[PDB]
Image (spheres, coloured by chain):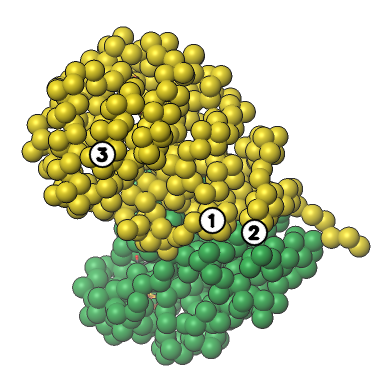
Chain colours: A yellow, B green
């Protein structure tokens, strides 16, 4: 005479606990990231409910420009732009400011409300390039009216002050993977170098955007470790890339993830970080295909449009239509 | 928990119970915020009573235009100026070429579809029988057909040649049928369904969302399919045709469509429920939601007077949802 309960009850219980002020434990998150295919839609649904409980129904749209491309001394095993790997990538110096402003203007027409200057290379060690970056970041913000981001690699405290002064509101630095996996993906810089960078940005009063890449041979457990590590670092802006394997790099042959594995991972990040702005970045179109729309009703509330650094995306108008079709709104 | 009743009703159904009309009306009004819980529960009901396969079908427009029926939605009606291609029953070799293409595209079954009230000329009908035979026996697809109003004697002949699905949409709820057609009636459809069933053929019957029905009428439509023991249900979404009285009907919101699909699954837990016409146009990048939100079949390869996307994309999507084919 007791009704039979479904396999997905724990998902409901935990979601309720979080929406009532509790927190998921590591063991719980590990269980949830192993959710079945059959129960995945309940997990995604409950992530969407957590998202709604702690945030509005807006989707934050960003876009980037590869303002300086290729020729990087770092050996990050996934990156097209490393010198240790022949990938046939475009190489060029810092774009001229009018060219950058054009891209800024296109990103705004496309529906981005914030825009990142991204450069290859460890850091920006020449103080003249840095100065050019500051100059054009200012023009973007004051003349185009976009919030400004940047991804400049390793960052000193003095640089972060300057970024803060010119009006940067997100400083991007990805942890890439779980601390326990970072040695297996890069050796020319360390995890510690990422901590320094992130700390320096935070101490200058800049909200840090930090995430990483699913599909680097991390275990599911390590994806959970990565989320809690972001929690530790007080990160509330999280871009989740999915590896786009680059011919010539060592991760060329990395096995593709199953779309539902990716979507489950997104949902579990939401459970672990209920108040964060969590977004897709690289690899969305190619690795989620016709399931991309699941992300924004499965725990994510941001999207990078207009393509990436050395890899493309779909038309941003299709992305704006998808947001509308999901009955979500566009931020700011 | 604003979505608690969704969970309770779903669990009741999976423990052997039935949704009430009143409850179905409430569920079809689920908020946007609660829509994913509804789709999830419909996915659980689909899994509980069926399996994890997606049935892939395709069609050919074998005879086009010049229909004396005045269905307000239909491009092939003669009462409406619509610019539709008109042609009599296609030649065997063309039809077989279309069937080969469908099979290559991943369809397990294939429908000869005709404009018209019916086929009255017994010779034209035998031509239909002849080619149905060659499709099944030579190309090796299961065979469906959609020939309009059907007599018992016609149904026996289709059974004999090996037709495994006879298609005849009810289109809408009985209470809305007069508002879409007056050259034939709702009861005309009821005789056709009975005739096909009594000959031993599984009937495939659904209809069209977006014909100005109320949400309540969509529920009525599902309950009628329930009463009729229909277990193969194609859910079309109106593609408004220029020149028809419904050319200016408003598009439905994707989530409204998906909520409707989910509610049909709650009412018909055991049924093979598929998308048909207007899927790509009206669901766009939310099409994938249907197969993890209550549906378990898909029509690929485009329609009668309207196209579809690449079937390979459709097959990839099935695979990406961790579903199988058969
Ligand atoms: C951070 S930007 C370059 C700026 C600077 N060099 C740095 O390392 O911060 C390059 C970022 O794109 C992502 N990325 C690079 N190659 C990728 C690939 N093949 N697939 C997916 N994401 C990738 C990584 O997460 C990486 O943090
Ligand atoms: C049923 S077949 C034609 C065979 C036969 N004349 C009959 O009415 O049964 C045509 C089917 O396509 C669907 N259909 C027609 N025009 C449509 C449109 N504009 N949008 C969506 N579905 C449509 C209807 O459900 C209709 O039953
Ligand atoms: C820098 C942006 N922020 C982020 O987390 N990834 C974006 C870049 C992704 C690059 C994808 C691979 C390529 O285009 O080379
Ligand atoms: C006959 C098939 N089965 C069904 O229920 N609908 C299909 C036809 C869809 C037609 C869409 C509009 C057109 O192409 O004219
Ligand atoms: S991710 Fe950054 S640091 Fe690593 S190789 Fe690419 S450009 Fe260099
Ligand atoms: S009976 Fe069939 S072909 Fe004729 S108008 Fe109606 S749907 Fe169109
Ligand atoms: Na389903």
Residue under pointer 3: A165
Closer to the eye: label 3 or 2: 3
Count of numbered circles in the view: 3
Subunit that carries the residue with mark 2: B
Residues at marks 1 and 2 on the same chain = no
**Residue displayed at 63% across by 68% down:** B2
Q: Quadrant of residue A310?
A: top left
Subunit that carries the residue with mark 1: A
**What separation in Å lies between label 3 and label 2 (alpha carbons)?**
51 Å
Can residue B201 be seen?
A: no
Tell me the element at label 1: helix
Q: Using a 10 Å C-alpha cutoff, classify the residue at mark 3 as few (fewer than 14 neighbours), some (14 to 19) or many (20 or more).
A: few
Subunit that carries the residue with mark 3: A
**Residue displayed at 49% across by 46% down:** A276
Q: Is residue A287 above or below residue B44?
A: above
Q: Using a 10 Å C-alpha cutoff, classify the residue at mark 1 as few (fewer than 14 neighbours), some (14 to 19) or many (20 or more).
A: few
Q: Position of residue B217 (x, y in %)?
A: 54, 82
Q: Is residue B150 above or below residue A8?
A: below
Q: Quadrant of residue A311?
A: top left
Can residue A71 be seen?
A: yes
Looking at the rendering, in which quadrant would you find the C terminus of chain A? Answer: bottom left
């Amino acid at each position: 005479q007791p009704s039979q309960v479904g396999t997905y009850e724990k998902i409901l219980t935990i979601a309720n606990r979080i929406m009532n002020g509790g927190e998921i434990t590591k063991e719980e998150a590990i269980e949830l990231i192993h959710t079945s295919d059959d129960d995945t839609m309940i997990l995604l649904a409950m992530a969407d409910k957590i998202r709604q409980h702690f945030n509005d129904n807006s989707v934050d749209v960003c876009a980037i420009v590869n303002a300086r491309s290729g020729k990087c001394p770092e050996n990050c095993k996934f990156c097209a732009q490393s010198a240790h790997h022949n990938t046939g990538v475009q190489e060029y110096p810092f774009m001229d400011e009018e060219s950058i402003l054009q891209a800024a203007r296109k990103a705004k027409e496309a529906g981005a409300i914030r825009f990142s200057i991204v450069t290859s290379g460890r850091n920006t060690n020449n103080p003249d390039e840095f100065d050019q970056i500051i100059h054009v970041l200012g023009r973007i913000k004051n003349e185009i009216g976009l919030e400004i981001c940047c991804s400049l690699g390793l960052l000193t405290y003095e640089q972060a002050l300057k970024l803060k002064e010119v009006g940067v509101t997100r400083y991007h630095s990805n942890i890439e993977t779980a601390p326990s996996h970072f040695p297996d993906i890069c050796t020319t810089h360390s995890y510690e170098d990422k901590m320094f960078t992130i700390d320096n940005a935070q101490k200058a009063g800049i909200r840090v955007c930090s995430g990483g890449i699913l599909g680097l041979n991390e275990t599911l457990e390590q994806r959970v470790e990565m989320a809690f590590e972001l929690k530790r670092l007080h990160i509330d802006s999280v871009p989740l890339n999915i590896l786009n394997p680059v011919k010539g790099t060592p991760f060329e042959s990395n096995e593709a993830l199953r779309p539902l594995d990716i979507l489950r991972t997104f949902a579990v990040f939401r459970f672990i970080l209920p108040n964060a702005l969590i977004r897709t970045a690289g690899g969305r179109e190619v690795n989620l295909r016709d399931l991309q729309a699941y992300a924004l009703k499965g725990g994510l509330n941001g999207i990078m449009v207009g393509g990436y650094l050395t890899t493309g995306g779909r038309s941003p108008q299709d992305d704006l239509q998808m947001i509308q079709d999901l009955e979500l709104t566009r931020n700011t």
